[PDB]
Amino acid sequence: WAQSRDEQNLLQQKRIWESPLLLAAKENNVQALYKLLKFEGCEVHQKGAMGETALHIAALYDNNEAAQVLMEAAPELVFEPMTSELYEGQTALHIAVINQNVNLVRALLARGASVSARATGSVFHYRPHNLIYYGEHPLSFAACVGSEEIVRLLIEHGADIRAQDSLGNTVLHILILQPNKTFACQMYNLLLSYDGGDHLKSLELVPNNQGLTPFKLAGVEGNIVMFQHLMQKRKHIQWTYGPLTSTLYDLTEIDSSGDDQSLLELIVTTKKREARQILDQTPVKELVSLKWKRYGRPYFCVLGAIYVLYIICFTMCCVYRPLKPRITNRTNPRDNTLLQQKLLQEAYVTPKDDLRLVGELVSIVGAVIILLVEIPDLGGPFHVIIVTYAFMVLVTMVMRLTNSDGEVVPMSFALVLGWCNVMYFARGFQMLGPFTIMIQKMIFGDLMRFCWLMAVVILGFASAFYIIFQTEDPDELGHFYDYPMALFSTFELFLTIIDGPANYDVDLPFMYSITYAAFAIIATLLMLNLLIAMMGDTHWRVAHERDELWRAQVVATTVMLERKLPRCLWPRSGICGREYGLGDRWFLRVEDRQD
Ligand SMILES: C[C@@H]1NC(=O)N[C@@H]1CCCCCC(=O)O
Ligand SMILES: [Ca+2]
Ligand SMILES: [Ca+2]
Ligand SMILES: [Ca+2]
């Protein structure tokens, strides 16, 4: 698809070269323009390859003299938008605004150009393949390019600031998505002065079609500069007392008020890395930290203590299980067999099995609640693990209820998952907090990078160890008799977790001494590289990534508790405005100091 527009741009330049009219507009050849329009009368409405006019060409190459001649010789061309699918809707005013050609904009002003004309072309979509997203309307273009002169010049002649684009985004939303934040704060504040000024229907409330006001979009986008500028509207100051300044914050669109209206939920859900810094801002970081110090951290330790007691109950119900009498003469055939197994299907004997019978009941009623609080639908893995645990005890109470021969196969998956899920609560206390973040980011990151190389390497040498020690009885030295144990043992030789095949009472094969020497050297090389490849994330920037991503996870956890927990526990943060001078809304007191 990228070649299509490249072909069409090269095709356009060919049609610019072929068409002498469009050529004179590109080169500003005013002397040639008259000869083609008067002395050898051609079509002045001559369309280009992009459905453009000679005026559309004279617009992007900033030569007003060629555009002036076309609008004087045919004032019908101004209203015409480009008809091609790439550039559909773009008038000659759009190009004049985005190129900051103020004189062409003011000349198209006198022609009565459409200020409400929508540029719906595929090159104006908010997509990665478009280098920028300036919007739909020419007023949106004037605000994004950073020309306050064109913004006011457009509003003077009927430009509607409320006009929402293809994605229902107002011009205020579009300024948040721009790069130059420090300058665009004046443009945002400038555009708001033209608003009606009524307390209702203010343009700061007109939301994106994805339910997002401009103040709320700044947080999700990670625009730290706009979010601070957008905070002064929502900031009340109680008093100034020496160096201290008790300031009262609004907390309306911030914090858990509605379902998905809360900014905090939008910050933790969005994948934007910059959005985590809105959490560290003065109005919010004081909120979430106080939501954590009280009603946040204690309940997380309660659920932690409950879960630890819930699992240590289920774990204690797994060490004590129905007895496993071999009771078969199958143990003598196939010396490899090493099992004493099975159930005898009875839990009704009522001695001390009733203690683990209610322990099994607690596990099932706990799992069905776990499966009925999570499946009704970052700390993702440590929440998928919980439902797979509940899934694994629904396969350790159903197939195990019907007397399965291998009923311990899914009980081990249930055990390690829910047990290693306890360090989910490691984000509770500060010491273990950032440590659990480091192990999680390193699994998807650096485990795959070394495991695929380890897999390719062990596959090489485990096969070369199979092929040599298949040519030998495994009664002695039999470290890898068949291919499953060939991959398993060599995988273990790779991690120094076996003594390595070593038998000296009897002689070894000729090639093992040579092959394992190369293996031990490559095994340590890849092991040292694995040690120093994950070392790369020890930079001073990562030190913040170690700490902040834990805080971001704690705040993400802090919202996870309050959203589902009842209202009687954990009251609404801040103090309500009713019974005070304010108006039934909840505000946060934060006093600081300036040195
Ligand atoms: C130069 C092209 N000729 C023309 O008349 N309009 C085009 C404008 C190009 C803008 C592409 C914006 C984008 O990348 O989406
Ligand atoms: Ca060792
Ligand atoms: Ca040993
Ligand atoms: Ca070591």
Image (spheres, grey):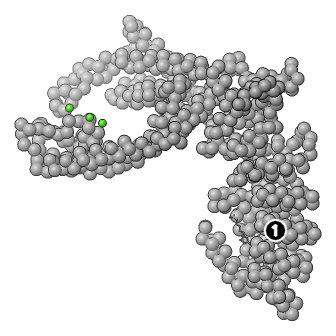
Q: Picture coordinates of residue 434 (x, y %)?
A: 51, 32
Q: Quadrant of residue 397?
A: top left
Q: Residue at x 44, y 28 (%)?
A: 420
Horizontal arrangement in the rendering, residue 301 relative to residue 420 (left or right):
right
Relative to 390, say whether 569 is above or below: above
Q: Quadrant of residue 233?
A: top right
Tell me which image quadrant ligand 2 sits in.
Answer: top left
Query: As displayed, is residue 392 above or below residue 99?
Result: above
Secondary structure type for disc 1:
loop
Q: Nearer the viewer, residue 364 or 400?
A: 364
Q: Position of residue 14 (x, y in %)?
A: 68, 82
Classify mark 1: residues with Cα within 10 Å, few (<14), some (14-19) or many (20+).
Answer: many
Is residue 228 placed above or below 244 in the rendered structure?
below
Q: Among all residues in the image, which is located at the extreme top?
A: 351
Q: Position of residue 465 (x, y in %)?
A: 20, 47
Relative to the observer, which residue lies in front, 133 or 533? 533
Q: Which residue sits at x=59%, y=18%?
A: 298
- Mark 1, residue position: 101
The residue shown at (25%, 23%) is 340
